[PDB]
Figure (tube, rainbow, N blue to C red):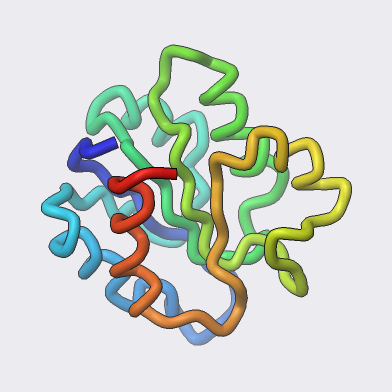
Length: 137
């Protein structure tokens, strides 16, 4: 929970990475470690490196630009009950929704250990990245 490990990346077509947008600065604001992959959706590949670095949380810079891979990727990592990564502050993740998610995160509402930053947030919300996840939920 206070593990120094933040694996960040993804994003689709949007300049380059307006998510990169120093969410890694929040690393510093968490006294955590950096595990920037890039703009890939390395599931089972960075899951092998999630044992390595010991990914505490995952920060996606995409509102579904990772598929059902990253969706039931970390949910499967919970359901793994071996790989630690039950904290997923998934930036963007599904547009036109906040709290009230469709049938998709209806089942992942029950899980709902993953929060999302609504489209139109700020890096001010990333100060709140590791403020809530490290604090209490």
